Length: 170
Length: 113
Image (cartoon, rainbow over all chains, first blue to last red; front, side, top):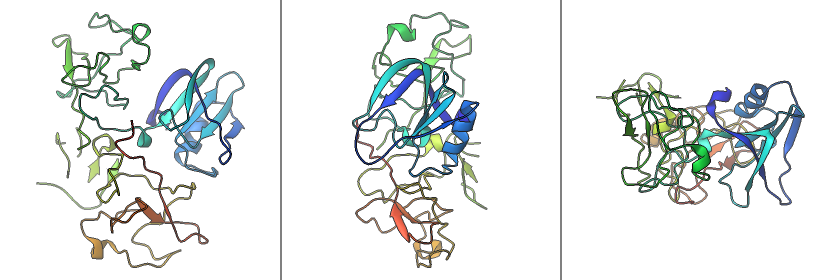
């Protein structure tokens, strides 16, 4: 069930306010955190994201994600952020500069090449050169915010790259 | 996926490059709302309080008149959050908690950048 969440390595979330209080629990694996979050079992709120503290092998369930207002991302080696896809906008507004969904296939049904890898295609689009553009896994993205919206490097050696088909909100 | 018992149109959904807009891939069904949410057709099925939603076709624990038949086109399927009357408050659902009849669901607006 953890494959249903968008993973963001070495990241945690922080939000301050009265009302809601994060839910925590020591477990053995992150999958356990995903299971409880998906089924939303025993959670006094609707879980939009969770963090697996790989150090304390602890879990943190949040009634919010990185796009929620008043929430901040923070780097952390022991942390791993998992966001529920149902709450990450799955359509784009215009050029899709800010698209952060999990679609990872071109409009030709060709699977995408991970960004941090150079096989089969060599490129200069490494995450470290685009801090803030979320170039992870093989998710379609628009790092330079160009027309033609989100795209990715196809795994097909015959095709270097190809835009992905992501619906307009309208 | 978003199941729709006994149905079909005339890989987004199954295998066509489009869907009714039966199993439909959630990535190709807008998961955010514009305004009231009258047109919302996503799969969120838990309220703003974490309570799982009661199926629309069920009369327990809460008896109601929002029958799928009386609201054809409103997609009152399973226990998905909806807003069939396009009311202010946004998509909602009857809850599985006998003490809480209904409650809105926390679905974000599209134009929320």
